[PDB]
Amino acid sequence: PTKLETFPLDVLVNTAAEDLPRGVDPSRKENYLSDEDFKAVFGMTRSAFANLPLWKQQNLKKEKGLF
């Protein structure tokens, strides 16, 4: 698919789901973080995160306000 746009961490954490930017899926907020923000928040590669069990992906996001 088309490369996703990048959005600041605070926009993703503070904006209600229905108020988010066009193209932004609130169930996949981590995919819109810049590489710098993703690395800082999750401390692992995107592929590594995507390969984790769903419960773990969700739990890590919950502790960061990204779920």
Image (cartoon, helix red, strand yellow):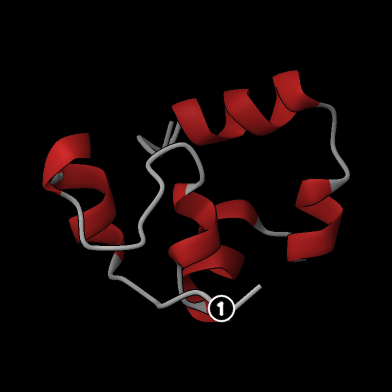
Q: Is residue 37 above or below residue 31?
A: below
Q: Is residue 6 above or below residue 9?
A: below
Position in image of residue 55 (x %, y %): 72, 18
Identify the residue position indicated by label 1 in the image. Answer: 35
Q: Nearer the viewer, residue 2 or 46?
A: 2
Looking at the image, which residue is at 54% across and 60% down? Answer: 31
What residue type is disc 1 on?
Asp
Looking at the image, which residue is at 85% across and 55% down? Answer: 48
Looking at the image, which residue is at 14% across and 45% down? Answer: 15
Looking at the image, which residue is at 77% across and 65% down? Answer: 45
Q: Residue furthest front?
A: 1
Position in image of residue 37 (x %, y %): 46, 69
Q: Is residue 45 above or below residue 52?
A: below
Q: How many marks?
A: 1
Q: Which SS class for mark 1?
A: helix
Q: Is residue 4 above or below residue 17?
A: below
Category of crowding for the residue at label 1, using alpha-carbon neighbours closer than 10 angstroms: few (below 14), some (14–19), many (at least 20): some
Q: Nearer the viewer, residue 35 or 5?
A: 5
Q: Quadrant of the N terminus?
A: bottom right
Q: Residue furthest top?
A: 55
Q: Quadrant of the C terminus?
A: top left
Residue 11 vs residue 52: left or right? Answer: left
Position in image of residue 8 (x %, y %): 28, 69
Q: Nearer the viewer, residue 48 or 22?
A: 22
Residue 63 in view in this figure: yes
Residue 16 in view in this figure: no
Residue 19 vs residue 31: left or right? Answer: left
